[PDB]
Image (tube, rainbow, N blue to C red):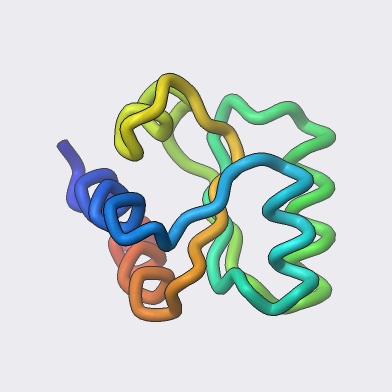
Length: 99
């Protein structure tokens, strides 16, 4: 019931999210993603890969929640890697997480 979880749900409604390690990496490289959210549960190699890649592109990465909470927020069961495709959502989600 956090504000950022609710907002993530609206982003999903608006079809402004991508999920999956490979899909999100590709989207980052194509300049289509302005924030990456990683589950705290994500494997350390997944964490490394995203943090390395997004570091190079200067895309913020947040490590938050768990895969159950993230999946639920977007009407799915479990998700570990989420890419946000809308800059406005990206800014606001980051601010909420950083608050």
